[PDB]
Image (cartoon, coloured by chain):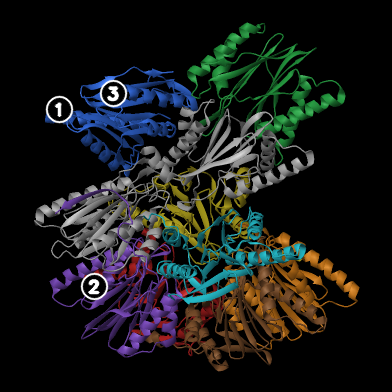
Chain colours: A red, B orange, C yellow, D brown, F cyan, G purple, H blue, I green
Amino acid sequence: TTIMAVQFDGGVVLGADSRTTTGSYIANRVTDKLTPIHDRIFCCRSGSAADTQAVADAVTYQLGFHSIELNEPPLVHTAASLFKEMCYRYREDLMAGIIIAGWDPQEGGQGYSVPMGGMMVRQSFAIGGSGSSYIYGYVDATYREGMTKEECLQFTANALALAMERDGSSGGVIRLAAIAESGVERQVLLGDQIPK
Amino acid sequence: TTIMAVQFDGGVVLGADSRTTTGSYIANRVTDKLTPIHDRIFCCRSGSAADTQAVADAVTYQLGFHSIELNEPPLVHTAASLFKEMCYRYREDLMAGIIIAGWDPQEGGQGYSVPMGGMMVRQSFAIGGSGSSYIYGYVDATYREGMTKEECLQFTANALALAMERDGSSGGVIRLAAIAESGVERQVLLGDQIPK
Amino acid sequence: TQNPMVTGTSVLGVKFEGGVVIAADMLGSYGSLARFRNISRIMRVNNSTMLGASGDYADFQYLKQVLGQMVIDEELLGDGHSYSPRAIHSWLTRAMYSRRSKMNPLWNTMVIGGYADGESFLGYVDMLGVAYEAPSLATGYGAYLAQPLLREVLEKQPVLSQTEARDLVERCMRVLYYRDARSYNRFQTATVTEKGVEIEGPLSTETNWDIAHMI
Amino acid sequence: TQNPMVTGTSVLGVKFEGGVVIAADMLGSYGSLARFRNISRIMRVNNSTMLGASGDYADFQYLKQVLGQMVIDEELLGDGHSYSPRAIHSWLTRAMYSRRSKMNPLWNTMVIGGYADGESFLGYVDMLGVAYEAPSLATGYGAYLAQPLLREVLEKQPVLSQTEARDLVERCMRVLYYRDARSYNRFQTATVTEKGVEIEGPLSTETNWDIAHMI
Amino acid sequence: SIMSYNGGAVMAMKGKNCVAIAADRRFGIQAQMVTTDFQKIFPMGDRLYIGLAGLATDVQTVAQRLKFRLNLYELKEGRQIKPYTLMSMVANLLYEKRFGPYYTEPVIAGLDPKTFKPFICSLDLIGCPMVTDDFVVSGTCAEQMYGMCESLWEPNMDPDHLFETISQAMLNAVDRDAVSGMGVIVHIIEKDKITTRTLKARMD
Amino acid sequence: RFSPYVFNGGTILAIAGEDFAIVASDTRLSEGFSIHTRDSPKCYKLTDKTVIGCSGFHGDCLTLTKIIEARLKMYKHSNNKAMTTGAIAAMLSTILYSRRFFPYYVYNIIGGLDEEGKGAVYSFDPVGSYQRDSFKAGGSASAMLQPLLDNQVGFKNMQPLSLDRAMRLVKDVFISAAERDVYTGDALRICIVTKEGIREETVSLRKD
Amino acid sequence: TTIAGVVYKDGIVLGADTRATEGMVVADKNCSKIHFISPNIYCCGAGTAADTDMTTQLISSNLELHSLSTGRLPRVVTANRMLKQMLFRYQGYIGAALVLGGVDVTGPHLYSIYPHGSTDKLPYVTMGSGSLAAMAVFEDKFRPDMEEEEAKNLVSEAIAAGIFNDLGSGSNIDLCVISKNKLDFLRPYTVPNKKGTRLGRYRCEKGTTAVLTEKITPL
Amino acid sequence: MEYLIGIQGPDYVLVASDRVAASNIVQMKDDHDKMFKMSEKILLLCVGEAGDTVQFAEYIQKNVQLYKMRNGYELSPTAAANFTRRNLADCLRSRTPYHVNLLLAGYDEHEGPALYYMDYLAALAKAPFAAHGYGAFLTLSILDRYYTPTISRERAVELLRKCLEELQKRFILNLPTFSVRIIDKNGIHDLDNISF
Amino acid sequence: MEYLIGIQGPDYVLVASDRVAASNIVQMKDDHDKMFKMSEKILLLCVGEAGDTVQFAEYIQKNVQLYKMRNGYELSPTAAANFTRRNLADCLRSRTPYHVNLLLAGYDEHEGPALYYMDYLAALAKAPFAAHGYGAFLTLSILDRYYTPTISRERAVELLRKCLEELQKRFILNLPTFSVRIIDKNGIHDLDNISF
Amino acid sequence: TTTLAFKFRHGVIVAADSRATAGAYIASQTVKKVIEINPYLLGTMAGGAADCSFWERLLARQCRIYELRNKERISVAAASKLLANMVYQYKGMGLSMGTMICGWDKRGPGLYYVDSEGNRISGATFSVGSGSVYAYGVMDRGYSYDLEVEQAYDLARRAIYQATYRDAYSGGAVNLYHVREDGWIRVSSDNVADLHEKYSG
């Protein structure tokens, strides 16, 4: 698994691969690891599939009820905090790392990382997953401030492809999502379009 | 530990860091991990210090005697296939990975990697050590054919510095060596000259 | 908390003529990876108390939200009473010990600094409930590297000044950067005085690598 | 060899009308890292024998050295006799079993192909000394993924031609690439025929990702 | 193992308009005999029987709880139980103690009280029904009984040939098991009578 | 750790008659839940009147059958005679016990004709102890095959063998055992040793 | 065991074998592994037999109650939700692996559920011991928008490969076809294997067995 | 390890048990009584773990006497045996198991004499003669050899004496004296102790 | 577990040992002899592990007799005890240790009577009375209570009888018969067996 | 397994069962457990069958070599001593065997018991195997040194039958042997399924 999010002026870019294995056997090769918690908030998931799916469903329920009560669109920080509380309460049971990313009118496009242990922190770019150890130097060297929306999709695709070639648990297709005020744009990069 | 070697037309470039730890305590911080096996042949060492030092001494002895008998300068392949049998014969005892690099008139400048287990393989660029997992994507993205001697002394420093910033077992100074026909050029990059 | 996961390294503290100073670096390591490099491990509790914690970072973040609400609730009463630096030390010891006995510890080492009523406080709380007070403090590997360095100054000259303590606390971040594998070159300082709590950072240390040429 | 370290994945083999064909990929994985990506795991022993081995790579190189020297020594005599595929199969079985009983095995699985005296040979040798012969062979996960496909074809049409066997080989490689975590997209083929041994590679497979759009 | 602490063997076979159920007679504690006339086949109706093999305490407990429930059911409903319903009842009773299971494996044999159509079935440790058409076995000597029954059973057996077949299968199967045997009891369930017989077997 | 053994399945059977012997086996080679081959017989011809069958771990079977043949040739060269069935059994016992502290994981049966022309069947355990029988089954489905032989040949619990009757009985017992044993049955190989020598036969079983 | 399912242009095809073993001895030769859940939803179970039986029965009763109250045909997403929530509640001690499938007012749907509460929505799925041997066939010969007969042949080939290449699978093949207008439950579809004919006559003549005691109970 | 024996004749039941209470390698007591009276015609002999024996036996005695006092008539031997078995079986799987081995001897005015055997797993058997202990192995063969269903009282006492002399000769434990009792239509009679 | 006792008087040594050979829970012999004659005035009593006892005792006997035959005079009790201790101590740390407990009784024409004690770790002590076994605990207190250095032969036999009656009363193992011997200036005399 | 042997005025009498099992499965019921070392010595097997057979064959060959060299037959005590010394050097490796050795020599009848742990004891009555504790009772109640030949035969048969009745790993047929001054003879091999009707009635 390799997941990543990058901030740009006006929104966030999320990317993931699509392989789920059981040992050395690829149980699924077209997995979708980008899940919409609300209209403009997404999470990328890594770890045990059961734990991440159950926690995402629970947080979706709670955030929807909160939004209906308050009669307002929710914040990214609220969803990050709900995930943090559930991950910290059951840290002896769950095995789940999450990236939260979204856009809210109060603070723009933001991204938070909730690793194993129920910690929470904000970052300009955030990588996670088993295959992310092979692209730390690349993202350190290549990232710069003031990137445009179209310069963040290419950077994300390059980093994910480089992680895919070297990791045994990463593969498949590359799924990208761009989140800004107007909406969410989703796309898939098949085998011909993956950088080489 | 992070060690690396790169081939260019006419020779090889070797680079290493300088930290040796015992747990979480830095026992030595100005270590020299580049040891000349012969006038034009070097090895970079990673793993247990005792095993690597003893094997380097034994191979130095054997290679010197062989060269005195044959009345010729030795080959890089000979030194690599002298390291290989000692590393394979005692694989249940030793814990040592090595990079062999040098220049011989028959095939120019070459580089071999002898990992744990006694394997042998030749490569255009070869990285090793505990801290090398963080620069696989970088060296995959940045390497190109036809580099010059000075474009290899700068790519090596960049890769090593990127590995140093993220690994806990890597640090100190950067030691570089360039090997070609004329001789061996050695230099040290202190804190001010290290790329940022 | 059976396993520590993302952790902090060490906290330093020393008392001077009219207040206390605490220092800590900005890094959270996940094993040996140095993963988060701009995290703050120093808190301001109220206008005379400051806190610094090492160990698991999720537990520190939890204690931070539990201790912030307890201070907020008491200022709502508007009665003229505030918690002393010593009241938080006493409360923290009870909180640690009550979880030690349930076999569910909080993986942290805590350093409390304060200045109230013309008397300076520097206190140490441990994972198991071991708590005490001293003129200088260091947790983790600073108990081996930095504590000998402070306890030599604090015997020749038992009473320091603000500048003498600020120089001492930076001479110890250099030795602790040279010889600790989980350190970083960016730290942060907090000072409590009669005025209040002042946080300054990030700072950096100048190093010397001359010996690399005698090898 | 108590631990495998750098390993290979799987070897495929099938016999046709006038010879044998063997296929294997070009990757050596260190755990889950995919570290060496241009290594060759197929050997040519002599003008009618070829060998392909999976498992530890150091042991495979050692057996390459021993087998090559044995062939050279037996060729130096110039008496008109040469080793057949069956002699190599038997010698390998003896060596593997003799090393098993010392509790120091060679971590490998090997496929021997050959064509001599108008008859083709395809044999399988295991780590413990289990050895046998079959019309088609696959080691590792290929025993689960590729073996059903080969046997389905071989039951209906017992005798193939060269092109049919080739095409069957690429189909099996494509399935393995889809469903195996330690695979790679570059493989290599060796064919033994009345002319001799001929190695072709590296090759590649064309994939299909239409189902990604019905998710 | 716990299933082999006491030993035991029970089997059921289907004929034409009749069924047969057989069990061994021995109670011992590992390698020592204690008694011979131990009961393992219990009647649950006019033409319905259940046989228990495994651990003796669980055998008796399960039999008594099943009789409890069956009596209450028959008092409320006012009719006789059906073999399907009894099998489902036993499966429920066994699954209720999942993670703490009773160490028995029942075998049920009877006739439909409305149509007199034969029924034989067997359940596993935690209650998974498995209905057959020819024969079911249970106990420590299951392999021997499978071998004998695959070779001797033939469709449409009248009571005499069915009795001979089940007698021979049980005798030759328990002659090769160390902790089973010392007598065989056979019940032949038919439309209008029930026949109970005790066979002459080795006592060693 | 490292385990020096695996279980590869297999069933062997022997019946001794008035003036013949029969040794039968199946030809499936398996490992775990997979199938290696469907054409791997387990009967080896030792002499024109002696056959041996082995089952268990396959590598031990191969090495043991090579050792036995080497020893038979050594004996023939030193003594100027062909070794006898009793001598073969007595030598195999010593060979098997030589590895007492790292045993062969094999089950062995020897069938043939004795010196008066009558059938002989000897059965072994993995350590060496052997016994002369009248019929014997070994391997995966021994517990299923033995009661049938006891009932039909020994006439147990009831109030001579022809060759044809023995053949029918062998085919029937393997057909019945193919139904219930996981490890058994792709084809059946039968070897009949009589006055005229050794004859062979094959039959087809279930495939699933 | 081997259970497989495919989605074609009009509905779902599910298939399974019929052998049930206990250790290394065949216990049942005609087991049934395709379970009724709703007139438009079916399930194929693998793993521990008792757990799959009880799980499917409970979920079927709950869906029956829900459909009675609302008055509409149920949805596959509802059954998937209840199954996955119940399985996650037990932390993986119910060794049930399920292939679930059905057609509703939205169209064909096919899910795979694991013992820990995971779920995948896919166009073709396999589970069991012989899951790899059938997945090879699906990877080789699957096309989108097949017809009914092509999908039935594909599922039969996958199940046959699982039967013939795995020791824990065998006997017959069962198929279930779910379409918007019908539901076919073929039992059995193919009989690849047959028992050989007996050569001897081992019938025990009357009087062969000696009897100690005897009693007659006239009903 | 304690020894219990019971023999069942045409119109009586004879029971015997040893009289040693041993702790470690020394005998603490030599007139211990292991024979509890549940009624005027029911005896219950118990051996096994220390503590469990007396607690279990006294609980059973209290309940049997309470049945007598409430209902005006006494429990039959069969019902008492079934009650004991149910109470041991219920506690088998709880947090407080009893490790006890039991013999129950009784007389009923309509069904005659009765002797029951129970082990610590709560399986109840009815036997014409039974034994508990390590001496059961040495004694049951003599009892099988010399017992007939029509044996009389004097012959039964002689057979018991044979069994106890066998224990004296062959068995390694020091068991000098045994207490003997008989149950008949006139109640429970204490016979002379057999001592060596 | 076997029992050995020795008492040492002014001009004799009295020794006794039991006569049981038991395997598991059954006695297999009741006239076993555990007393080896090394000379005309030396006895060696040995107990402990099965097999080691007879091998060790017969080795010692052979060597002592060989000394006699070569030199023309017999070994004194002290030298035999020292020889035995050295031979046990040497084997202690090898691959074939002996698990044996020993008493040695002898008479010397100049040094008088002698009694020696040795445990399985090969530490040699000289005592006026000694015991081995589990009955040593029960017996040594009586011996301390009633022993005087001037005790005579009949009084010594009476004291031994007291000790054995104590074993009969208190000890849990069945030890019916004991063999008794005495060593004096006239050699070794066999006394009447003490039986109960 | 149960084997017994007792010594009386007219010599030694040895009895054994015939069943051999492998777990809970009865491998065979025709095992010959009285090993015929010589025309003048007898041995039994209990524990491992392979160990007993192998080491008693070695003993037989040593006895024959001794007789060839010294022109005299070996005695029972010497044979038992040889067997005891050949198994003490594999102590701890895992052998398991227990044997009576029976004979007649210059000092009369002889009956020794040797096992792999190291014991070697002479006696007048022995029983080994799983079901030996069941044979001690009957044998002790019935044994006397002045028995007649037929009475001793009956005692041995009854003891073995009672042992197999209550033991689960013991059964088959009762094989009986008698050791006299001029060699041993084979008395009978009686099936238990017929002794049952002989004794019960």
Marks 1/2: CA–CA distance: 58 Å
Task: Please give the residue where the numbered disc 3 appears in the rendered image.
Answer: H182
**SS type, badge 1:** helix
Q: For the residue carrying disc 3, how many other residues have a C-alpha within 10 Å: few (<14), some (14-19), or many (20+)?
A: many
In the rendered structure, are the residues bearing label 1 and label 2 in contact, judged by CB atoms less than 8 Å apart? no
Residue G37 got which mark? 2
**Amino acid at circle 1:** Met
The quadrant of the picture occupied by the N terminus of chain D is bottom right
Task: Please give the residue where the numbered disc 1 appears in the rendered image.
Answer: H69
- The chain containing the residue under callout 2 comes to G
Residue drawn at x 72%, y 37% is: J73
Seen in the image, is I131 located left or right of residue G164? right
Circle 3 or circle 2, nearest the eye: 3
**SS type, badge 3:** strand
Seen in the image, is C167 located left or right of residue C67? right
**Amino acid at circle 2:** Ile
Q: Can you give x and y, in whole percent of width and height, for residue C35 in the image? A: 51, 67
Considering every residue shown, the one lying at the far left of the view is E78
- The chain containing the residue under callout 1 comes to H
Mark 3 or mark 1: whose residue is earlier in sequence: 1
Q: Quadrant of residue E28?
A: top left
Seen in the image, is I5 located left or right of residue A65? right
Marks 3/2: CA–CA distance: 66 Å
Work out whether disc 3 and disc 1 sit on a shared chain.
yes
| Vertical position of residue B33 compared to residue H174: above or below | below
- The chain containing the residue under callout 3 comes to H
**Amino acid at circle 3:** Ile
Circle 3 or circle 1, nearest the eye: 3
**SS type, badge 2:** strand
